[PDB]
Image (cartoon, rainbow over the protein chains, first blue to last red):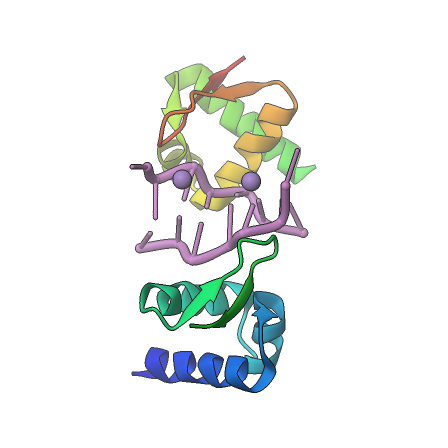
Length: 62
Length: 62
DNA sequence: TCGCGCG
DNA sequence: TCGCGCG
Ligand SMILES: [Mn+2]
Ligand SMILES: [Mn+2]
């Protein structure tokens, strides 16, 4: 699905750029912050990423 | 302002109907839930309403 | 001590 | 144990 494909792009972004906050990932994938966050939290449910518990949270690959 | 006027309508709604959750107020004022909540929390800052700490919160007049 | 992803 | 108002 297109959501899966968007998630793949987010994973590629983190692989290429290292740990990142949502606002940065959103600017590069070119999606609004809420949409990026929807994907980041699904990716966390699916054990592909984790967040740092900072505010703002820092995201990276599992 | 129009925001003030919207807030007045929400207050009138609570005066006429008694304590209410946001979803109910939204349906009657005919505004989306987020907009109603924006107003309810401003009205709380301005000491005109309070919420019950229930989930969903129940709102009423101070 | 805004974290918010919420369907 | 969705509370979400967020500018
Ligand atoms: Mn908080
Ligand atoms: Mn909670």
